[PDB]
Amino acid sequence: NLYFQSNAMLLPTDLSENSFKVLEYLGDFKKVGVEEIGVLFVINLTKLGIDIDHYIDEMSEKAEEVLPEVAQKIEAAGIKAEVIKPFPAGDPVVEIIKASENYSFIAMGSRGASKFKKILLGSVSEGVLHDSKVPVYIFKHDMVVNSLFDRVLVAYDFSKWADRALEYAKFVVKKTGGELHIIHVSEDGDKTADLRVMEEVIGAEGIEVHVHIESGTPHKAILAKREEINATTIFMGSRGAGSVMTMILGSTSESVIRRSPVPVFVCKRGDDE
Ligand SMILES: Nc1ncnc2c1ncn2[C@@H]1O[C@H](COP(=O)(O)O)[C@@H](O)[C@H]1O
Ligand SMILES: [Cl-]
Ligand SMILES: [Cl-]
Ligand SMILES: [Cl-]
Ligand SMILES: [Cl-]
Image (tube, rainbow, N blue to C red):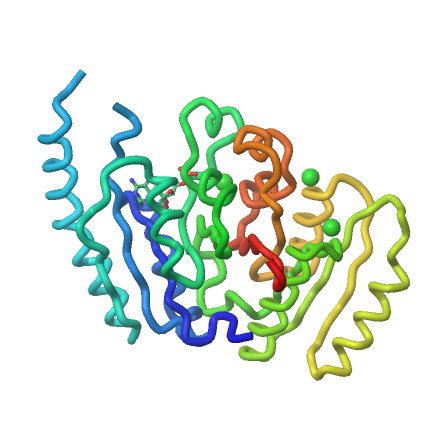
């Protein structure tokens, strides 16, 4: 495959500070092949007591003041920028997913809300993560700019989603010369032997790889590992099962993504999907 190679990247924004964190990593994305970024602002009608055409207009004017700054910063990094127009009005989650059919992946922010606040107030990032078919990359902080793919940690369970997460990971580590780290969590249903074998095969493929077997709650073991080896990003897979509600309440990805100090890339389909 081409992975990030010649990628168009979808960048949703509600103009919030958290939505712009992605922009601190433009150098990292350029170095893996991202060549164009589509910037998507949605007039959020979902929330709606007040007239809903002055609102489209209020919102449109705000975007037009700010988005050119976004476009500017992208151009300055030597990446093509397109402010998507006209601005869709409706549900941000639906409009983002709709638009994403035209892109290789989605890079977006999150306010890092607790499970409770996500449920109470809504979470665009969880909605997107739940239904997206392209990968979704969540950025909250700038702790690892210029180092994004130096130490990639892959949460890996042999599933088709993890498999493709591993392949993206191998791609970036090959591009940037970093280190690949693979963690698999499980009490048993022992797959240690196979994982060890893969460490060896991947080493032979010219990549520096370290495999980690761990016990306990998945999100706990994953974050603990990230700290232990100072991973610069976490790659993982998600089948997006159940409902948004169910994902928020009990998914491994919601917890990992929420408490992670580094960006989390989430693969949303297998190679043969
Ligand atoms: N009206 C909107 N238009 C475009 N993107 C949005 C909008 N609202 C939220 N988002 C995206 O959702 C992220 C926040 O995720 P969350 O905190 O889970 O709602 C923001 O950083 C944006 O990337
Ligand atoms: Cl795992
Ligand atoms: Cl978990
Ligand atoms: Cl979050
Ligand atoms: Cl982050």
